[PDB]
C-alpha cells in the first residue's frame, strides 16, 4: 500500500515499472465528523499558506515595497 | 439545539478516545484511570463570530 | 584464628517446612549471622507468583460467570495463594480447562515438563452446573519483593484487552522464619555455638539453595566495604 511493486507482482504482468509514484489509486468520499478538529487545523494551515502566497505575490513581485512605511 | 453524546470530541489525544465506542460510551470493563473521559458530551454554542 | 561455619546437616521434617543447622560458630557471632540471615531470607528471594489471568467469559473481576458458586473476585483471591515453581524460563503461560461436577485443583492445570506444581491438593473453586466449563489462562513470571497491581500499570504498552485481569503479586517464597542459638558439640574445646534455623515455605524453594542464595547476596552486597 505504501509502495507498489511489479517484480514481485509477476501475476499482474508488471503493467508499469517498479517504483512508479504516479497517481494509481482513487477514493470516493470522507465524512470525518470526529476528525473535524483535524480538518479545522488543516484548514488553518491552508489559510496560512494561502496568506503567505498572497503576501509573496503582492510584495516580492515588486521587490517588497520600496516606499516609506511604519513599523 | 440540543447537545450530542457522540464521539465527536476535539483537541484530545487518540488514547483518550480509544476507550470509547462508536456511540460515545465506554465499553463494559475498561480500566479507566483518573483524568479520562467516560462519555463524550459536546454542546452547540452560539455563533458569536463569523 | 576463626572457625568457618560449614553446613553439615539438613532436616526435612516435612515437605512444607524444614530446618537447617550450622556447625562450629565462634561466640558472639550467633546473633550476627542468625538475625541477618533470617532477615535477608524473609525479605529478598526469587518468587514465582501468578501475575495475570484471562478468564474465558468475563469482562471484569466483579462479574459472576454462570455455573460457578464463587465470585470471580473470590476466584482471583483464591488463585493468588497458589504456589508454583518455575525452572525453565522467566515467564510461562499456564492453561486450565475442566468441566462437569466437582471442584478444580492444581492437578487440573496442564503440566508441561518445564513447570512443576508443588501443591496438587490446593483447591481453586467448586463447580455445580453439569455442563459448566471454564478455560482460564494463567500467567506467571519470576521476580522479587512485593509489586502491587496499581504500580505496574506504568508499562503503558497498550496492555488493555478487555479479557485480561490483573492480580496482586505475592513474591515471597518463604512464609515463617525462626532461628535460635545453642551450645554446639564439644569440638575438643569450650564455648562452641551452633544455631538452628527453622524455615516455613510454600514448597517452591529448598532450604539449602535458599541459604546459598541468601549468603551469596549478603556477601556480594557487603563486598562494597573496601574503601579507598
Image (spheres, grey):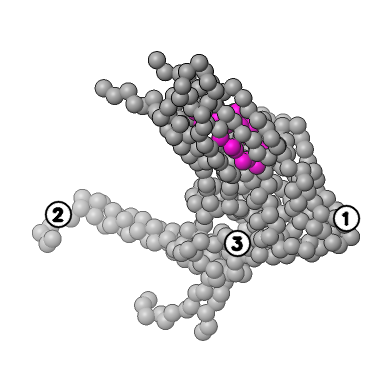
Give the percent coordinates (x, y) of residue B6.
57, 71
User: Do the residues indicated by labels 2 and 3 lie within the same chain of the protein?
Assistant: no
Which of the chains bears the disc numbered 3?
A: B
Q: Is residue C58 magenta?
A: no
Query: Which percent across, then down, holds residue B21?
Result: 61, 65
Residue linked to disc 3: B30
Q: Is residue A24 visible?
A: no
Q: Which mark is residue C100?
A: 1
Please tell me whether residue C204 is drawn above or below residue C223 in the rendered image: below
Q: Are marks 1 and 2 on the same chain?
A: no
| Of labels 1 and 2, the one closer to you | 1
When the figure is inspected, residue B32 is found, relative to residue C113, above or below; the finding is below
Residue C88 falls left or right of residue C99? left
At mark 1, the secondary structure is loop
Residue on which disc 2 sits: A66
Disc 2: host chain: A
Q: Which residues are magenta?
A: C197-215
- Asked whether, in this view, residue B42 is left or right of residue C120, the answer is left
Res. A45 image quadrant: bottom left
Residue sitting nearer the eye, B3 or A65: B3
Q: Position of residue B8 (x, y in %)?
A: 53, 68
Looking at the rendered image, the disc whose residue lies closer to the viewer, 1 or 3, is 1
Regarding residue C206, the answer to whether it shows in the image is yes
- The answer for how far apart the CA atoms under marks 1 and 2 are is 94 Å
What percent of the width, then of the height, locates residue A12?
A: 72, 36
Q: Quick one: label 3, few (<14), some, or many (20+) residues within 10 Å? A: some
Residue at x 59%, y 38% (from the top left corner): C199
Q: Nearer the viewer, residue C132 or B35?
A: C132
Amino acid at each position: 500500500t505504501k509502495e507498489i511493486t511489479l517484480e514481485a507482482a509477476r501475476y499482474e504482468d508488471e503493467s508499469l515499472n517498479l517504483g512508479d509514484y504516479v497517481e494509481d489509486q482513487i477514493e470516493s468520499v470522507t465524512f470525518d465528523r470526529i476528525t473535524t478538529q483535524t480538518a479545522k487545523q488543516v484548514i488553518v494551515q491552508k489559510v496560512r499558506e494561502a496568506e503567505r502566497a498572497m503576501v509573496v505575490d503582492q510584495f516580492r513581485e515588486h521587490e517588497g515595497e520600496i516606499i516609506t512605511g511604519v513599523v | 439545539g440540543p447537545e450530542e453524546i457522540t464521539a465527536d470530541i476535539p483537541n484530545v489525544g487518540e488514547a483518550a478516545l480509544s476507550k470509547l465506542d462508536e456511540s460515545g460510551i465506554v465499553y463494559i470493563g475498561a480500566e479507566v484511570t483518573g483524568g479520562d473521559i467516560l462519555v463524550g458530551k459536546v454542546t452547540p454554542k452560539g455563533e458569536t463570530q463569523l | 584464628e576463626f572457625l568457618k561455619p560449614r553446613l553439615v546437616d539438613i532436616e526435612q521434617v516435612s515437605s512444607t517446612h524444614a530446618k537447617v543447622t550450622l556447625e562450629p560458630l565462634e561466640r558472639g557471632f550467633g546473633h550476627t549471622l542468625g538475625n541477618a540471615l533470617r532477615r535477608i531470607l524473609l525479605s529478598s528471594m526469587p518468587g514465582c507468583a501468578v501475575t495475570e489471568v484471562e478468564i474465558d467469559g468475563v469482562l471484569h473481576e466483579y462479574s459472576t460467570k454462570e455455573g460457578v458458586q464463587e465470585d470471580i473476585l473470590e476466584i482471583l483471591l483464591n488463585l493468588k495463594g497458589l504456589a508454583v515453581r518455575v525452572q525453565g524460563k522467566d515467564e510461562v503461560i499456564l492453561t486450565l480447562n475442566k468441566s462437569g461436577i466437582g471442584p478444580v485443583t492444581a492437578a487440573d492445570i496442564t503440566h508441561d515438563g518445564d513447570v512443576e506444581i508443588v501443591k496438587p491438593q490446593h483447591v481453586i473453586c467448586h463447580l455445580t452446573d453439569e455442563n459448566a466449563s471454564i478455560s482460564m489462562r494463567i500467567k506467571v513470571q519470576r521476580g522479587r519483593g512485593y509489586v502491587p497491581a496499581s504500580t505496574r500499570i506504568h508499562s503503558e504498552e497498550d496492555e488493555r484487552p478487555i479479557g485480561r485481569l490483573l492480580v496482586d503479586a505475592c513474591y515471597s517464597p518463604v512464609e515463617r522464619i525462626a532461628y535460635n542459638v545453642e551450645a554446639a558439640r564439644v569440638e575438643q574445646r569450650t564455648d562452641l555455638d551452633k544455631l538452628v534455623i527453622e524455615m516455613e515455605t510454600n514448597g517452591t524453594i529448598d532450604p539449602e539453595e535458599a541459604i546459598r542464595r541468601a549468603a551469596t547476596i549478603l556477601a556480594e552486597q557487603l563486598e562494597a566495604f573496601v574503601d579507598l
